[PDB]
Image (cartoon, rainbow, N blue to C red; front, side, top):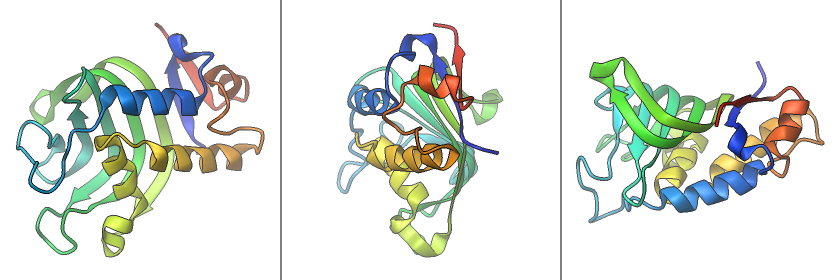
Length: 183
């Protein structure tokens, strides 16, 4: 199945690039970097976890923004290749106010703004930190949505070359890719 997008009507007239660049800035950078990793402050969590799951979720330390990565995901911690997120990335949900977790029937967003599903990304452990799944998610953690933008652009172009991250959500809805949700 092709990429499927869900968007709050708030973003009807925004391009996908407009939304993602502004979201990266609103979420900011959690500084999950050497000498700055703080368990429970800038690490996020897996469901079921601790280092594997169908979801990885992280709250901003700048705002109430949060994201949920969905698929079949694995983090290597100190194991070779160290600090690699790999596996299948099927979806990215962006918005505000993370709720739930493993004990609560899964992570959710109280204010889901935009979701991208059927991403079809599959990065093997052998690629380590060079894998697309790692670059997409570590980008979101660190205030840089360029890797996600590039993958969405390629998926949209493959549906029809008139579609791109410079398409508005309303243009993608007219093309049958995207679906409006309430504001």
